[PDB]
Length: 166
Length: 167
Image 1 (tube, rainbow over the protein chains, first blue to last red):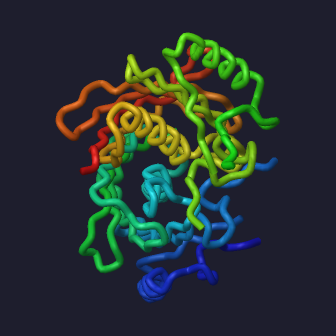
Image 2 (cartoon, rainbow over the protein chains, first blue to last red; image 1 turned 180 degrees about the horizontal axis):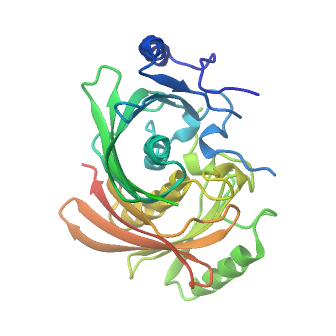
């Protein structure tokens, strides 16, 4: 029984810093860290050995209906030379907005994902994916997110998504 | 000396092999061409051992500005239990539409990807991604695609995209 959403040696200084900061936010119970555990099937985002692929941890604020994913993209996520593949970014966006929708609505299927890639993300960077449930209409759950640098000054990507309650 | 990965290996299901054969036949007259794919930093879509991750091959038709990707998603691409992660589907879509733009007009970067998922794709299934360069306005390349079953009776996903040519 391994929880992948706690530090391991591959974690960069920036990821560790934000992790500590969000763990502090959990102290009053407004935020909560989500564990991420790991016939051949494996969750895509946890299918790389430590450091090589997706390194991440999600924190959830139920009152705000907000899911923040701290994400460090490893060398096997390359697309354009030196940058994280558009698909890998989309994968972490999907994972974050999808978990946000699931916390609010239970089991849901992804219906639409619409991503604006504003600036390319350097390989081995740490980014913060801030997602939020924007509205619920019957069985429709609308979630948006941003992907930003640790200092919040660089906006890498923005996305909207729609999930449907099964 | 790099191994071309866009060819059959023992992990390939028979329906993928049959469709591969059909597209190799379409290459006969030169209209279509199979794209070699080769493998620190590694191309995301080639970072798994055979069969476990992305198994795919692209065929390009230059006169049509059309790119077809044959894709079999392995067990390590799971999202919802038993199905391909939406991110993995988005990855192969991005790979296909991005390569279509690149073969037509050169080095580009993804600017928008808008994916409608109509039906979930079972894990270890084979699909065909058919993409088309629809228009070009300056540095802007507009590419759309769909994702279907091999027999084309099931529509899994549709997408539009925007790529920007680098200066």
